[PDB]
Amino acid sequence: NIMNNPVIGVVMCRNRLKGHATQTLQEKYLNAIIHAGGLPIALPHALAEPSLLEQLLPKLDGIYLPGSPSNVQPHLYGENGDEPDADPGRDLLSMAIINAALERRIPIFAICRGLQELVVATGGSLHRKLCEQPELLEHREDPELPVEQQYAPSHEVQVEEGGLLSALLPECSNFWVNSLHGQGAKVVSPRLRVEARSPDGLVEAVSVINHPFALGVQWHPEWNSSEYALSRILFEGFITACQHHIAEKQRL
Amino acid sequence: NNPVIGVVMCRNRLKGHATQTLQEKYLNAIIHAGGLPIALPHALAEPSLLEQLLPKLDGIYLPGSPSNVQPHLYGENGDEPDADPGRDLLSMAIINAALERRIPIFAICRGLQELVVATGGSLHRKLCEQPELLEHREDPELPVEQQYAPSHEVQVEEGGLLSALLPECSNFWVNSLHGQGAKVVSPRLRVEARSPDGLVEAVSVINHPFALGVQWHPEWNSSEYALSRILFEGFITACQHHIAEKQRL
Ligand SMILES: [Mn+2]
Ligand SMILES: [Mn+2]
């Protein structure tokens, strides 16, 4: 691309490899940003410190919340108990950087866990076990199938008109998405607008009202994003918003 | 203000997915010394992306890694089962870019070996196959606390960077967790320290304000070690001078 590439801050996840706590970022989340024209930089959880975060935000043109096997701690939306696979450090950074980016009108694109981070950060709640709700489809992947089958198309979603997805996808009101999540949106705050739903009524995409571009999707558009026309448009729209944010940063 | 430190990541396979990784003990050492670390994915090795990102960096941080530099990058041939070509590409590119821009560099273990290769040097791929050398590798079966325990001595070569940060002491003990080491050191570099067997354990780039590499692991509980604390503080101080340099232009 003949392009100045906006700086995209990518929230990392925590893992432990060979005896050491490690900050990680899957390459497929990176490849999708690159293909769309972004300049990604990975953000460790230590940056959640307020004095460091305030110094970094002016240098970020967009915030990128990847998915992850971990689930948000239930106490962050007022519930008791725990769930398997927690990442309290990512929770800390995600909540802080979302709230900061929403006040600074920095574009946000959130995937799977990121959407759930968006819902919780703005006052919503999550279903902790979608499989325990009889009215819903099976939104989880089959973990014993190979990776390619896990990210294959799983169910359809229907776009709710009047939001970001309608502007980005004028023709498509309905399309196929993959599904790899055992948790999902339960209560969505009035600060958020519903963007799409699976045929069982589950919210699969949201966006922040009165924000230029704060979009979350429950599926995984980063999966071979260059090969999927719909995934390409979503990342293209995110980068275009960051370009607009750069241009808007000189009309303040 | 805390200088922005660009940290080179490593590639790993986790749950069947290629993943860029960065151990927290490298990040914690930068945080304690006063730096603001951001992790640099391998895809940033693209020249256009690197050129856009370098003005926003105040220093470059090359951590250690289990992986080794591919021998063809210094003109040799051989197998390397634990390789990371993505890290190899980014490290050489950002080292070269940082050397031309006078951006401070601090490199650890694999970072030192990257410094030697990027400036025209070579490496010993099997230190264990040389009977004159000490055992520089760690025992992977011991607990991690004694894996990073002090293992052998080093002697500072006076007149360089290490003599500026530690003018009083020329000899100290360091941990050792490497099976590879510097062989030929280019004249662009000056030797900063050697172990008693003669192996180079620290280098710095002549003609540069602060481009230092060490073969040991000073990030391990860095705040609790006198030498480790001094090395990271000197790196951050170097980065602050680079910030004032950019603001004067
Ligand atoms: Mn789903
Ligand atoms: Mn050694």
Image: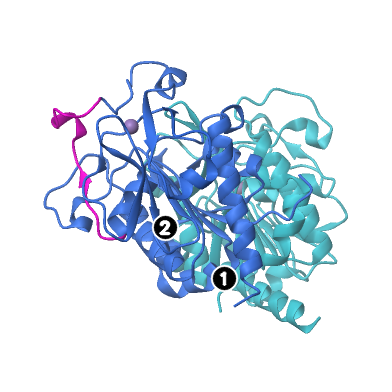
Chain colours: A blue, B cyan
Image coordinates for residue B150, horizontal then vertical, percent: 49, 54
Whether pointer 1 and pointer 2 mark residues with C-beta atoms closer than 8 Å, the reply is: no
Q: Does residue B237 sit above or below B131 in this rendering?
A: below
Image coordinates for residue B151, horizontal then vertical, percent: 51, 50
Label 1 beta carbon within 8 A of ligand 1 = no
Q: Quadrant of residue A128?
A: top left
Q: Main secondary structure of the magenta part?
A: loop
Q: Amino acid at mark 1?
A: Pro
Instruction: Work out whether mark 1 precedes mark 2 in sequence or the reverse, and give the earlier one.
Output: 2
Image coordinates for residue B189, horizontal then vertical, percent: 82, 57
The residue shown at (46%, 61%) is B28
Q: CA distance from mark 1 to mark 2?
A: 18 Å
In this picture, residue A134 sits left or right of residue B234:
left
Q: Which mark is on residue A45?
A: 2
Disc 2: host chain: A
Q: Quadrant of residue A211?
A: bottom left
State the residue position of label 1.
Answer: A58
Disc 1: host chain: A
